[PDB]
Image: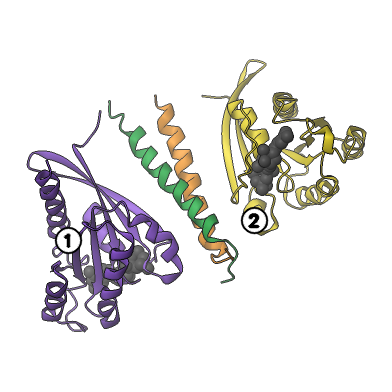
Chain colours: A orange, B green, C yellow, D purple
Amino acid sequence: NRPRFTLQELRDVLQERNKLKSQLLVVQEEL
Amino acid sequence: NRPRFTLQELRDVLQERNKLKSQLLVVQEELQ
Amino acid sequence: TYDYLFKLLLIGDSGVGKTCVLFRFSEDAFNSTFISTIGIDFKIRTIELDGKRIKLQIWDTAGLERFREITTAYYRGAMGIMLVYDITNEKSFDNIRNWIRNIEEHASADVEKMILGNKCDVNDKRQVSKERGEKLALDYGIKFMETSAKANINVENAFFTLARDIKAKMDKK
Amino acid sequence: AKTYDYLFKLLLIGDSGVGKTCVLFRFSEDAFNSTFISTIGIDFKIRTIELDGKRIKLQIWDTAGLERFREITTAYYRGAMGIMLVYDITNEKSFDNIRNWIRNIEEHASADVEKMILGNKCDVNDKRQVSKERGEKLALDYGIKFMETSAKANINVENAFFTLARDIKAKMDKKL
Ligand SMILES: Nc1nc2c(ncn2[C@@H]2O[C@H](COP(=O)(O)OP(=O)(O)OP(=O)(O)O)[C@@H](O)[C@H]2O)c(=O)[nH]1
Ligand SMILES: Nc1nc2c(ncn2[C@@H]2O[C@H](COP(=O)(O)OP(=O)(O)OP(=O)(O)O)[C@@H](O)[C@H]2O)c(=O)[nH]1
Ligand SMILES: [Mg+2]
Ligand SMILES: [Mg+2]
């Protein structure tokens, strides 16, 4: 419903999401 | 600090992060 | 692999079609469901130009103001930027000036820019004629196209034209 | 192609700061870091063990204890096959709250889920607030297995997870 989480909290998950995305593309290519 | 993002917004990003972590492991499977 | 890596950025008001334009470019598909972007996302597509392999790393920003700090972080690396409005939403067209100001504040002065008037399939709700988009782009000295993620109009053309223009400037240096 | 014969979904719950993430870090990486980084919502780690000549993949979900994340964490109760209820032997309130976590399991988890109570930080007995006898008595009252653990000193961490997994497997084998 209403806002609850901070900028740093969302950001840390987004940054990890991005890192995993990039890592997944490297391994997918290794093929 | 100041609340800015909703439960749905954080949940959604956490679920994608979780999905990617599992996918990374299953592609890593290729120890072939 | 590739010869060049081009970092691209899509900016514009929430709801104008940035994610759907990118979905058409990367998957050649369209869906009418609105899933607003949480902060930022990116997609990769590699193309061939004049004998070179060009990896396009395309960052898709959230348009809502609450994501400003998150999206500001991606202007600095950008080599080309699509400024997107919705031809059915004059307010989103007026806000292109604000998005341009943000580019000038945070991006390189030599960044390639292009304006996209998206949703050109929805003429039954059009609020901005194409001539107004052309004139805005002309005044800024940049290119303009009306696009449709839904009808597959000018999406491929927009990205290939932007990449060609980046490559041409780079090659001359 | 599958690297396992069974997949067990485990869940760690309990108050913030009791050591859930450290227990999992000790189990999955055999290391310990004393710098507190409180979990944002949910995370998971993997470890595959061998039981009865079968490969058992343990997918271990690590919940945030803080009340602000409850709505995120409770969605992960339903699929859990085993749940660790963790308290801190130096923190009496975390022990009292075990009754509340038990109630949350009853509301959100499967009726037949396997459960185990861990009294963590058993390396620090000078600051101990909860006696082992009191922990054993609470677990007996609720009919749940009990161990005192230490992620720091590497006490009973493998024992806890191996035992929980053996209990899950015996039930699955019971229904054949
Ligand atoms: N008819 C039509 N609808 C479109 C077109 N492009 C996008 N839409 C619809 O417009 C809505 C918004 O599209 P999105 O791409 O999600 O908008 P966005 O610019 O990414 O919005 P934010 O992520 O919030 O910044 C969605 O319901 C789309 O289906 C188009 O070319 N034609
Ligand atoms: N002495 C001692 N300290 C421990 C032990 N396990 C964890 N700690 C400390 O307790 C603090 C909390 O540990 P965490 O694993 O991060 O706590 P948590 O239960 O995951 O907390 P939340 O993620 O907020 O729910 C950490 O700084 C650890 O260093 C232990 O076995 N012995
Ligand atoms: Mg979007
Ligand atoms: Mg934790």
Is residue D34 shown to the viewer in this render? no
- What residue sits right under mark 2 in the picture? C67
- What residue sits right under mark 1 in the picture? D157
Sort mark 1 into few (<14), some (14-19) or many (20+) by Cα contacts within 10 Å: many
Report the chain holding disc 2: C
Q: Above or below — where is C14 with respect to C1? A: below
Image quarter for ligand 1 equals top right
How far across and down, in percent of the image, does residue D42 sit? Answer: 39, 57
Task: For mark 2, give the secondary structure.
Answer: helix
Query: Hey, which quadrant is residue C172 in on the image?
Result: top right
Callout 2 amino acid? Phe
- Distance between the alpha carbons at the discs numbered 2 and 1: 42 Å
Callout 1 amino acid? Val
Q: Residue at x 61, y 22 (%)?
A: C47
Q: Above or below — where is C74 with respect to D69? A: above
How far across and down, in percent of the image, does residue B29 sit? Answer: 30, 32
Q: Residue at x 50, y 45 (%)?
A: A18
How far across and down, in percent of the image, does residue B18 sit? Answer: 41, 47
C-beta proximity under 8 Å, tags 2 and 1: no
Query: Hey, which quadrant is residue D4 in on the image?
Result: top left
Q: Residue at x 65, y 51 (%)?
A: C71
